[PDB]
Image (cartoon, grey):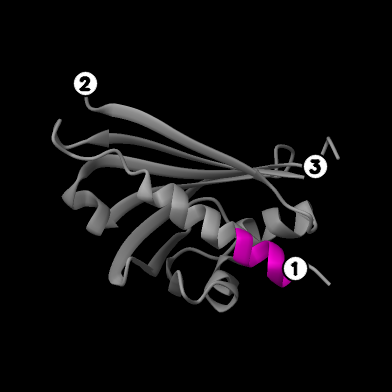
Amino acid sequence: GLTGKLICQTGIKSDGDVFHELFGTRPHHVPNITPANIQGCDLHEGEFGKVGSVVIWNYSIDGNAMIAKEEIVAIDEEDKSVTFKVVEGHLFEEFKSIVFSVHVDTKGENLVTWSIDYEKLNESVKDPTSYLDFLLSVTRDIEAHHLP
């Protein structure tokens, strides 16, 4: 009853490998490129670019500042994907679990796919569609930054 998945896909005209490695090896640069959405990214544990690292995101939706501590649970070079599991923060006021994944397909003529997998604390919790608007805004800012 409490489980859902939200996905958004959009094209980018910028380099897809650079987009993938931004999230997979340089996630601390993301605040600098989309500062209206993401104000901070601090290493909590481990090292940037390694599975099992833990980062703290300081970010904002609708003017409201929030915090998500996330474990990087997967970095797949072959699939150009990175998977972030929330382990603490504002989201845990609504969800038992919530995992964000970003995948880039460069095989066609580039697609960014964000997935949100989650389990609500109860049925009155809203599905987190606002986070797709947020991830699309982040993606548009990154594309614009990486374009000549």
Q: Residue at x 45, y 45 (%)?
A: 100
Q: Please state the extent of the stretch shown in magenta in the rendering.
A: 140-145
Q: Which residue is mark 1?
A: 146
Q: For the residues marked 1 and 2, what is the alpha-carbon distance in whole angstroms? A: 41 Å
Percent position (x, y) of residue 108? 83, 35
Percent position (x, y) of residue 115? 49, 39
Please give left or right for residue 1 compared with residue 110 in the image: left
Q: Quadrant of the C terminus?
A: bottom right
Q: Name the kind of residue labelled 2 in the image.
A: Gly
- Label 2 element class: loop
State which tag comes first along the sequence, 1 or 2.
Answer: 2
Residue 139, quarter of picture: bottom right
Q: Which residue is mark 2?
A: 1
Q: Name the kind of residue labelled 3 in the image.
A: Thr
Q: Specify the label residue 106 is tagged with.
A: 3
Please give left or right for residue 69 compared with residue 136 in the image: left
Q: Quadrant of the N terminus?
A: top left
Percent position (x, y) of residue 22? 66, 62
State which tag comes first along the sequence, 3 or 1.
Answer: 3
